[PDB]
Image: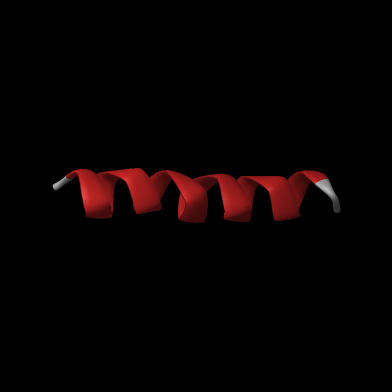
Length: 22
């Protein structure tokens, strides 16, 4: 699960980071 769970963080952060950067 760590693979999906670990990677899931990157995706979640990726979207959040993009939103913050406008």
